[PDB]
Amino acid sequence: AVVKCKPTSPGRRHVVKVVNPELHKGKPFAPLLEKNSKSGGRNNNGRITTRHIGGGHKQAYRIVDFKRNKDGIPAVVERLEYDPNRSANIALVLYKDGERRYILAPKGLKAGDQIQSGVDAAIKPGNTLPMRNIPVGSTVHNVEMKPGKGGQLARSAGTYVQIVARDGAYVTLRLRSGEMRKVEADCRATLGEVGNAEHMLRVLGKAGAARWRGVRPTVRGTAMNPVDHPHGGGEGRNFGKHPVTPWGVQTKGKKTRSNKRTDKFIVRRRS
Amino acid sequence: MKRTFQPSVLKRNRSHGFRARMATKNGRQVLARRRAKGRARLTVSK
RNA sequence: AAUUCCUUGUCGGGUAAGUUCCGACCUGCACGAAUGGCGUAAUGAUGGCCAGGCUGUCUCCACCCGAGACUCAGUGAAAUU
RNA sequence: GCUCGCCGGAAGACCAAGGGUUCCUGUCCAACGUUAAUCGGGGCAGGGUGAGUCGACCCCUAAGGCGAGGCCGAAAGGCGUAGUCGAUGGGAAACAGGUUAAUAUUCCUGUACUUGGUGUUACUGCGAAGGGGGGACGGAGAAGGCUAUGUUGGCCGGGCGACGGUUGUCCCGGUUUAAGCGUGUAGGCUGGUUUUCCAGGCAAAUCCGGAAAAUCAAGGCUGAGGCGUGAUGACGAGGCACUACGGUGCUGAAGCAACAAAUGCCCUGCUUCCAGGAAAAGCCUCUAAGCAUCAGGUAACAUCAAAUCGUACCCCAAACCGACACAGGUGGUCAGGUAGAGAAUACCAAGGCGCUUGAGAGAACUCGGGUGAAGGAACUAGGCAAAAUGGUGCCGUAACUUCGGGAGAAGGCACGCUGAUAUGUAGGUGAGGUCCCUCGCGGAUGGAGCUGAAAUCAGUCGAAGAUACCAGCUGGCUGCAACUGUUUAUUAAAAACACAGCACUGUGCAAACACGAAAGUGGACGUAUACGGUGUGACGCCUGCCCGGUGCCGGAAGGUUAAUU
RNA sequence: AGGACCGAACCGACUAAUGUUGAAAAAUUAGCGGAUGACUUGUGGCUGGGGGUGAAAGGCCAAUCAAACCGGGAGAUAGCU
C-alpha cells in the first residue's frame, strides 16, 4: 500500500512510499541473473549522448521471459520479487517440468496461482495467447509487436492494451498512450494488467532519492551562457526567444516523428 | 598544495611508453622525428 | 517593495535626537499571477534593525611578558640607476 | 656523560606509491649545508639486499584496451565477433627464538606446512572447449560470546633510604612463550535417509531441478576463543670468570590468578530497510564423443622438484610532488598509562627530538599575548576585533507550527574533600562445595574472592569545587531562498545553480534524441505509471483577460511557385 | 528510522590578523561549515580543442582558457611606436 512518512526531518516530510509485503524478502534466483554495468549516458565513443544519467545503486539484471513460448506446460507462481531494472514486479514461476523463469507480475497474480501459454490455454490473467484466440475487447499486456520476437508493449507498472477490433489477419489495439495501432493477429499477448498501479503514487521527497535512481541534476538552460544553450544568458532573467532544445528544435508542439516506414499500423495518433 | 605532477610508473609507461607510441601511426611518426633529431632517449621507457 | 525618480513621501512606533529599521496609508515615475502572485513552520558561516550580557572598540591610553627592530661576530640579497 | 625542554592518534613504529644507494664502515672538508664544522642525506673508497611459504611472475576475470575474419569509410582509418590483454578484486603453503657495523617470516636453531613430477603396492569407471553446485558479494542497526590489551593481587629477585618517618597495608623490576597438530565449545544455517517416475539444464547424465511414496527423528555443514600438545625447550630480571671497559661463554629464580576490556574476532552471521546490493577461474560433482585383461582415478609409502625477479634505505619526509635541507601536499597498518563520553584535551610510557647562525642590549615602532581605575559601543560604514557564554543532573520553558518542531527556548538550583549508611552498598563477575548427567569445553545449586557506581545524611577547607586544558552568548522584528546540498582552484558561497513537487510538449520502439561522412553505440537489454526537451521550483490558498503580432499545430478551395518537359 | 542533532579523524574555506622581493606563484594563526551521505578517499580506465566536461561561474581541461599546448604556413599583416 501507500504510506506517508512522518515529518521527523526535512527530506522525509514529503516522502511517500509504496510498501508491498507480498514481495520476496530474500535474494533472487541466481541462475537468472546477469551483470548489468552502468553506462553513465556515454556511448562507445565516450561522449555523453543522453544527459542526466550517472551514479545510482548497483543493479543486477534479471532474465525476464518476454516471449512465453513454453506452450502446454502449466506453471505455478513461486513468489513475487522486486526488480530494480523496471517499475513493475516480476514473478518466479515453476513449470511442471522443473524449469524456472521470470515473468512480469499481472494485476491480481499471487503465489500458488497457475498460468499457461499456448493457443489452448484458458482466458485468465497471466496466460499468454496469440491475439487470434483473445476475445475482442479484453485487456492484455506484454503485447508482441511482431510474432515471436517477445513482448514490447504495455510492460510498465500499470499499463495495458485494449483490443478494439480484429480485421482478419490484423488486430487493432488501443495503446494506453492513445494510438489505435494494429498488429498482426499472431503476436502473443498476456491477459490482465501489469500490477504495480500504486507505483505512480510514489513521491521521492528529496533530491538524494532521485540520485539513487541514477538521475543526475538537470540544468535549465535559461540559467546558462549563450555559448552553451540557445536560451543563453542576459542581465537578469530575459528569455526573449521561443523555447528550443540545446541543439535548436522547438519542443513546444513541433512533432518529431519522421519515420514514414510503417505509416500503415497507425490508425490514430493520440488525443 | 597538490601539484600537477603525481608520478606513476604504470601510467607513465602506458601513456608515453615505447609500445604505446608504436601502437598508432602518429606515435610511430613521433619516434621517427626523434630518431631523425638523434635523441639519446626515444621515450620514457626507463 | 531586492521594484518609488521626485523622496529623508506622510502618519505612528522605537531613540534626548532614527536618510536605516518596524507598522500603516496608496499619488504603483516604472508590482502582478508557473521568465509564477501572495503567505509560510523549520533551516541559513545569507541582508537589515533593536535589546540584555560583555568588554581597551572608544573617552584615553598605561604597564608588563615574548619575537623583531638596535649593538657585536659569521654568511650575505633585491627592486632601481 | 649529567641535567633541562618538546612530541607522544606522533614530531613514535611498519609499508604501498615515488625516489634509486640517500643504507653500513673507513677516510677527506675545497665546493654543497643560508654561520663554524673535526660533523652530514657532501667528496672518495670498500662493504651491504641470501625465500617452495612475503611480493611480483603465474591461473582468473571487472571497467576498459587491442582485435583473425567481418561491417563501414576518399586515403589515413572507425566499430566490433571469435579471441587475447587488462587489478584497484578471486586463487596452494612458516611460525617462534637467536644472529650482522649494515639483510632476514629470506641466514642459523627448533618445530611445521602446501602444490606438482616420478616410482611401488592395493583398490578401481576414467574421460570436456559441455551441464550443475560452489566461489558470490548492499546499507543500517542490535546485542551476546571472546581475544588483543590493561589494572590489581599473588609469586620471585633486589632494596631499607643524601633531610623528619620508612621491616611494612612499604619501594623498584620481572612474572614472556608462536605457527602447527588434537579436541570441535559460545553460537549460526539446514529436517535426514531409501526407492520409483519426469515436456527442464542446447546432446547425454547416477549430478541439478521437478513429482509421488515409505521410513526415522537425530543428520550434516559452519564456527571465534578456551584447553592439551608443541615446550625436560626457548626466553627470562639479575649473577659468575673472561672483560681492548668494545662485549661474549656458562648459570639464570618466579613465569600464576582475578577483574576490566575493544573500533579487532565469532560475523561473508543475526535483525531490519529499499535505493535491491561484480565477473571468471581454482575447488566439488555430472556425464558426451572416446579408452577398457589398457589408459586413467582413489589411498598409502618412497623419492624428486618448487624456477625467475623484488628484498638495502627514506616513505606525513631534508631521500616522494612543490626550482630550496621549502611552516604546503601525500594512501594503508599498529593504537600503552592517569583524568575523560572519546582516536577531543592535559600530563606521561615505549620511542624520537630541541626544528643548521649565535652573543648582547632591554629605545621608538611593528608583530603574538597578559592585566586594568571610572565609564560601558560614546568606536565604527557595521559590536570588525576583543571580551563574554561554555559541562553533567534535576526543575522549568513563550509566540508560532506543516504537530515533527520551536527547545539545549529563556531561567533557576546542586557540584570539592572526609566519614557513615555499607569496616565497598545496588549492580556486574564468579571459585570451592553439593546435586544431576546422553560422565562433557555439561546443567542446576552455591556463594568465597575480585570489581564497583549512584544517592542520602553529617562534618570540613578555600575568595572561588563543571576550579587547569577542554567547553553553546541569548532574546525581539523583518527581506530573500523552502530545506540537506552545489558554485567562479587563486579578491564574489549569495537572494545565484541543484532540489523534491508541478505543468506543457515530443516520443509506438529499428522510439524521439544524441555521438558518428558510415558501420554502429548510447537512450535501454528500457516500452507511455517509460524516455527526451523546456519552464516553474517544498507545502498552503491560487494562477485572471488577450490568438492582432511571432512560433507551433491543423485545413483544403483559390492565387503564386523549382528542377523537369 | 533520518540528504536528523552535538562533535574529532576526514573533506571543506565564512571572518579577522599576519604575510605581500612571503616559510608558501593563495599559505600560517585564532575562530568557522559538513561530518551515514547529492559523503569522502586509493588504484586503474574513458571523454580532446570550436571539442570535452560542467548541481552553470564562461567554471575547469597539467601554476596557461570568451576557444589548451607543441610544431608548421611564417620573416602572417601592422597607413602604428
Image (tube, coloured by chain):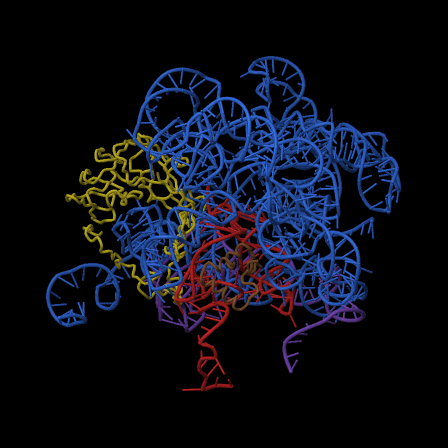
Chain colours: A yellow, B brown, C purple, D blue, E red
Location of residue C80 with respect to E43 vertically, above or below: below
Location of residue A204 with respect to D361 vertically, above or below: above
Q: In front here: D461 or E1?
A: E1
Residue A206 point in image, percent of width and height: 41, 48
**Residue at x-position 43% and y-position 50%:** A55
Residue D38 point in image, percent of width and height: 80, 59
Q: Is residue D465 left or right of residue D474?
A: right
Location of residue D398 with respect to A251 vertically, above or below: above
Q: In this view, does D373 lie to the left or right of A58?
A: right
Q: In front here: D291 or D488?
A: D291
The quadrant of the picture occupied by the N terminus of chain A is: top left
Q: In which quarter of the image is residue A64?
A: top left
Residue D224 point in image, percent of width and height: 58, 32
Q: Please give the count of numbered marks on the rendered protein.
A: 0
Q: Quadrant of residue E63?
A: bottom right
Q: In front here: D523 or A1?
A: D523
**Residue at x-position 41% and y-position 47%:** A37
Residue D144 point in image, percent of width and height: 56, 30
Q: In which quarter of the image is residue A31?
A: top left
Q: In front here: E21 or A100?
A: A100
**Residue at x-position 31% and y-position 43%:** A157
